[PDB]
Length: 247
Ligand SMILES: CC(C)c1cc(Oc2c(Cl)cc(-n3nc(N)c(=O)[nH]c3=O)cc2Cl)n[nH]c1=O
Image 1: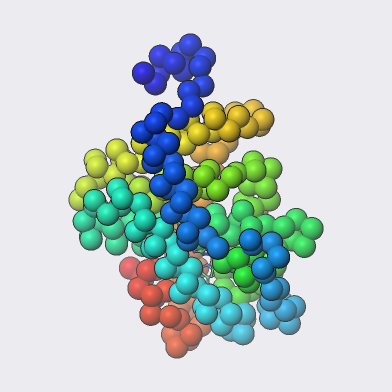
Image 2: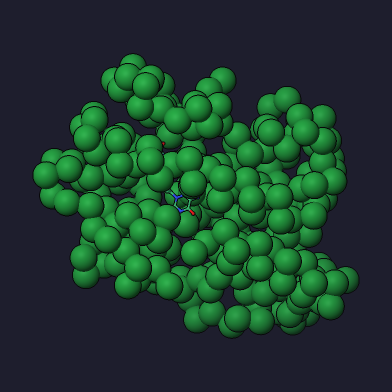
């Protein structure tokens, strides 16, 4: 099947089973990702440049952000086949990974701004000084890189699923079963990329490297959260934002 075709040099497009999964993951992403470019309103220059005034803007939108990731996971059926313990662990893990990817693809190089949530358009300094620190620099840096891949909404969606189904997080019972799901995404992704016919050499390896970069953004963010908990008062943290990134 897969590895013999690879030996021949055929780049196989998706199967009828995979197209059904591709449609599901894409429609899940599209529901949970709201005409972004005109819809944005820019956060002002005096906000930023931890700035608590800047922190306050993000924490309003962060409760929506977190639920958008949970509702995406909800819309995937394989996720629903897992237990609550594993589901909670998986969300707690990939939440900021999925959040960051989405912010990175909404990067405009003329204005030099990621557009958070498809509404709050911010600069590298604003997101940095408002809370994220060096995690701002990484998401911007990613956005700059992801601009020249030109990922469609399917490619972002399948990429998000890969991050969700990550068997290596601690406390997971069904580790074997999560690997099977990730593999079926990863294989379908590889196949969709062949249907797309991108004209960047070694595209698929290069795109897998961005999965690792996203996994770094999440880990660095876990450390930023600890600094945020020290620097900012707990009154300004929403209960869910605490719940998702604590412990
Ligand atoms: C400063 C602190 C409060 C903080 C800010 C922060 O910034 C972001 C926010 Cl509030 C949202 C998203 N985001 N999330 C989604 N679900 C989505 O569809 N689109 C999207 O842009 C992305 C980023 Cl980077 N991330 N984590 C943090 O801990």
